[PDB]
Amino acid sequence: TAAEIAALPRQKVELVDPPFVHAHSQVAEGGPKVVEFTMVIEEKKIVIDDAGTEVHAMAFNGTVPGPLMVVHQDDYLELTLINPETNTLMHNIDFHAATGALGGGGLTEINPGEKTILRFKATKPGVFVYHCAPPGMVPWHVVSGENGAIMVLPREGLHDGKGKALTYDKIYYVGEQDFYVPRDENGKYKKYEAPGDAYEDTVKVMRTLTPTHVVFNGAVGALTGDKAMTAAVGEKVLIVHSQANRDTRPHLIGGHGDYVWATGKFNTPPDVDQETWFIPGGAAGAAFYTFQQPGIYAYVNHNLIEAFELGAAAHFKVTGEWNDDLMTSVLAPSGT
Amino acid sequence: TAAEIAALPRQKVELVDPPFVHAHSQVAEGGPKVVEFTMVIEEKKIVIDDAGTEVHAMAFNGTVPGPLMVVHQDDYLELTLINPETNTLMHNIDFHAATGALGGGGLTEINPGEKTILRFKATKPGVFVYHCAPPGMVPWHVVSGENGAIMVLPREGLHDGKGKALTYDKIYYVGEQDFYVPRDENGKYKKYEAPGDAYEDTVKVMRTLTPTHVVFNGAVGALTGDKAMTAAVGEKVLIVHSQANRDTRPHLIGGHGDYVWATGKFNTPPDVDQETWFIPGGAAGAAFYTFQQPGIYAYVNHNLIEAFELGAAAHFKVTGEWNDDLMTSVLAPSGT
Amino acid sequence: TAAEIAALPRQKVELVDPPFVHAHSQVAEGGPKVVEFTMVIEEKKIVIDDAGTEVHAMAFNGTVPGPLMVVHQDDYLELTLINPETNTLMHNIDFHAATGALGGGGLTEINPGEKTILRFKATKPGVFVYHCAPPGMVPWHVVSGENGAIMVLPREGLHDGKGKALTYDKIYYVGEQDFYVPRDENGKYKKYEAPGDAYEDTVKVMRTLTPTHVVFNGAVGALTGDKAMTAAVGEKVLIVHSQANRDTRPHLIGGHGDYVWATGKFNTPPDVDQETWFIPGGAAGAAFYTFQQPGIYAYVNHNLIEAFELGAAAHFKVTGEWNDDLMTSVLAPSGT
Ligand SMILES: [Cu+2]
Ligand SMILES: [Cu+2]
Ligand SMILES: [Cu+2]
Ligand SMILES: [Cu+2]
Ligand SMILES: [Cu+2]
Ligand SMILES: [Cu+2]
C-alpha cells in the first residue's frame, strides 16, 4: 500500500506497433514491479481504403489501434503521455483496467505542449480497452482511432476452467475501428484541412450510427496479403481483439476459438469450441487456438457485409502438412 | 398448488418511482406470500431532451421506465393494473418472469376505463423485463416507454459462484429507452395532438432501426448533476439495467462490474471483473460493485455515440478518501 | 486417422425441409460412421411478404434456411453438393463445424453443371452455421438465403452443467434471415430478371446495414397460423436458431429458455432460466424448454420492431391443461 513500498523494481518497456506485442513473459518472473510505458498522441492524416479516403486520425504512437501494453496482476502500470505542441487538441486517457478518476482520464488532460505521468495498480486480470475521453468530445476522439488495449496476465499465466495451464506460442492484437467519413452531394468522401473542420460533418454521420468503414489495424486490407498474420500447424496462438465503440463478432474462417474469454476477463472461465464469439463495444476479448491445418484463414467480423464490404477482414497464413482425417475432398469439382 | 393453499400471507407494496427501489429484504423473511402491487398506465407528453422534444409516452405509474417490483422465488406477484378512462388505447402487460398466456398479456387487455388483476408464481430467480404488448401495436407501445422490470431474489439472497453471500448496501434501477421521434423537412422534431396522430410517422422511423434518442430514466440528463446516483467508498451497490427493445453495453467509467449477471438470471453464475457487459434487447441484467475510489463516475452505454450524442449517460457521485495505491498522478499535466 | 480406417459404417440420410429435422438418435447408437448427405443449390425467386416482394434466392435444397444436418461428435460428414446447370453462379460451402480450407469452401467451388464431395470429421460438439462463400461475393450469397446449420451431438446425448442427461421430445430449427431488397423512387420494392441484375442495387442497400425484412423460415408469417410449431404441456423441446450474418435475440413469449447454449457449443455449460438470449451473426444457438402451460406462444427476435414490423415472429401452438398455480386471472378486465 504505502508510498515508500512502491519504490519496487521498475521496468521500462518499448512498445511495438500493432499488431506484434512487446516482449513479456506469461508467468510473472518475480514480484510486483512498476512497469513503465511512454506514448505520444499524434494527430495525422491516414488513408483508410484503396480509393484514397483520408481521415484525420488521433493516434497513440502514430498507430490505429494504439499499442498493446502487457503487465501482470498487481503490477503498477506507469504511463508517460505526451501531447505534441503541433497537435491542436487536448487529450487524456481512460484505462478500463484502472479504478478511479474516470479511468485516469480526470487526471490526464493535456493540451498541445504538455505531458503527464499516471500510475495505477492492475488489480484485475484480463484484456481491457483504453482510449482518450476529452470532456465534450468523447465519441469523436475514440472514432478517430484514439483507442487500444492492455493485457493484465495472471501472475501464473493463463489457464482453462480446471486450472490447466494454457501457454501460447504467438500473440497477435487486432484492433477493429469504425470510421464515419462524410460525403458530398456526389457521394464522394470529403477532405478537410484540420481535424476540427471535420467535427460538424463527422457528427451528423455518427448520429446515423452507421460506419462508412470498419477496419482491422487502421485500414482496409491492412492485415492481408504481405501483412498476413502467420503461424504453423501445431502452434498455439492468442488473438486479442478490441472494439472501443461498437460490437463485433469475430470468426476464424476455417478454424475456431478453442478457448475464448469473450468478455476478456481471465477470472471468468472461457467458453470452449466457439465458431463465432461476441465482443461488445467498449471491451476487448481474447481467443486461444491451436492450428490444425495449413493454408490461408480469414479472420473476420461475422457480419459479412462489414467484413467484405466495409473492410473488416484479415488473413492468417499457416504452414504445415494437410490432415486428410480432419477434412478431405473426396470428389473435386467435376462435371455431373 | 391448490386454490385454498394460495390463501397465504398477503403483502401490499407501495412502489417508488425509478430509480429507487421499494423497500424489501434480500433474504426472504419467511415462507411464500402473495405480494400485491398496483399500477396505472398514463398516456402523457414528456420532454426528452434539453431542446424541448415532446413524446407521447405510455408510462406505468407515470414514469419511464416503470417501477421495479421485487419479490422472492416462489412468491406470487399479484398486480392490479388500471387503464384510466382518459386514456385512448387498450393496454395489457407481459412479464418475462411469468409462464403462460403470453407473459400474462393475453389475460390483461383493458380499454380506457377498466382494470384487471393478474397473479403468477415467480418460479425463476433473476431480473426480468415487463411491458405492454397490445396485439398489432407491440413495438409502438414499448418504444413509447411502456416497460420496466422486476427482480425475483433467491429466498436466501444473492451469492457468487461458490455460494458466497453477496449483500448490497444500495440498489439502483436504470431503464434505458430508445425513442424514435419524427422530424419535418427542416430537420426539426415534430409535435402531435394525440398519441395516435403520431403512429404513422413514428413507424416510418422505427423501420430504419435507428433511434433519435437513447435515454436513461426517460430523458437526456435525467440521472446527472443534481439527480446523480450516490454511494460512498466501501459500499456494495447493485445496478439493475434493462432494455426492452434493443441492445446496450453498460460500462461504469472509472470502475468495473465485480460480479455481473449479464443475462440477469441468478441461477446462471456471474461473470467477474467486467469492464463492459452486454444486455440484449428484451432483457434485464444486474452488476454488483464495491466502490474503491471517491469522485464522479459516468455510467454509460459503451457505444459512446449513443452515450454522448444520443443521451445514454448517468452520473454516480461517490464520497470517501482517495486511494493512491490504486491510482495516482505522478506528474500532473505540465509543460514539456 | 488412416485412409483405410475411414472405410467404417456409412449412413445415407435424407433431409427434411426446415423446420423438421431428419430422423436421428440423441445417444450415438454405435461407433463413428460416415454420414452421407446430398444437397442441390437452387437459384430461384421467392415471395418474402404478404405484399408480394420477390427475391432471387440461392437456396440449399430449395429452402431458406437450408436443412439441418445432424451427426455425432467424431463421425465424418460427407456431403455431395450439386450446382444445377441451369444456375448462373459458382457456389461453394463453408461449414463452421469444419477445420481447414476455409470451412471446406476452398475445396468446393463448383460452377453451374458441376458437383463435388467433401468430407470432414465433426470434432467439436455444438450447432454450427454453414453457408456459401464465393470469393468476391460472400455477403451477397449469404443474404440471399444461402445458409443453414448442422448439429454435432455429443456421443452420449445432451446434458446440463452436472452431467444430468437432457433428452428432448421434439426439435425444431429456426433459421432467421435478413434480406436487403432495393426500392425505386416511389418506395416500391424492385423486381429483376436474373440474380445478377440485382447485385449492384442490393449492395447499395447492404451497406446501410439495415435489412428491409428479417424473417423466420424464408418469409413473413412462414411459421405462423397453419404452420405454427406444436407441442403439448410436458414435452421437452429443443429449438435450434441460427443467424449467418447478423445478431438476433430470441425470446419465447410466455415461456423461457430453461437451458440455453447461447454460443451453441455443448462443451460450454448452458445458461439457465433465460428470458431472452443472444446469438451473434455467424453463429447458431440452442434453447431447451419444457412446456408448462397450454396456448399460443410467440417466438420472436426481441428487437420488437424486427419482430412485429420486419417479419421475425413465429408461433407455437401448445395443448394441455391450464395451470392456475403458475398464473391466473384474479379479476378479468372489468369496469372500474
Ligand atoms: Cu484525444
Ligand atoms: Cu471507455
Ligand atoms: Cu400499452
Ligand atoms: Cu417481451
Ligand atoms: Cu452461393
Ligand atoms: Cu462463416
Image: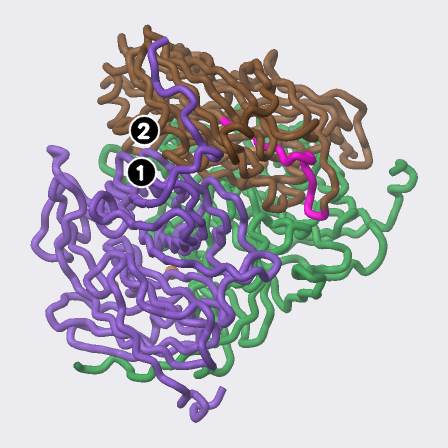
Chain colours: A purple, B green, C brown
Residue visible at 33% across and 84% down in the picture: B330
**Outermost residue to the right:** B4
Q: Is residue C29 above or below residue A207?
A: above
Q: Is residue A157 above or below residue A270?
A: below
Horizontal relation, residue B108 to residue C242: left or right: right
Amino acid carrying mark 1 in the image = Ala
Whether disc 2's CB lies below 8 Å from ligand 6 is answered no
Residue visible at 38% across and 14% down in the picture: C115
Q: Secondary structure at mark 2?
A: helix
Most prominent secondary structure in the magenta stretch?
Answer: loop
Is the C-beta separation of discs 2 and 1 under 8 Å?
yes
Residue visible at 69% across and 43% down in the picture: C160
Residue visible at 53% across and 23% down in the picture: B136
Taking depth in this image into account, of C14 and A15 the one nearest to the observer is: C14
Taking depth in this image into account, of C227 and B136 the one nearest to the observer is: C227
Amino acid carrying mark 2 in the image = Val
- Pointer 2: what residue? C138
Q: Is residue A96 magenta?
A: no
Residue numbers of the magenta segment? C149-162
Q: Is residue A115 above or below residue C100?
A: below
User: Where, by quadrant of the figure, is residue C140 drawn?
Assistant: top left
- Pointer 1: what residue? A307
Quick one: label 1, few (<14), some, or many (20+) residues within 10 Å? Answer: many
Q: How many marks?
A: 2
Horizontal relation, residue C160 to residue A303: left or right: right
How far apart are the alpha carbons under marks 2 and 1?
A: 9 Å
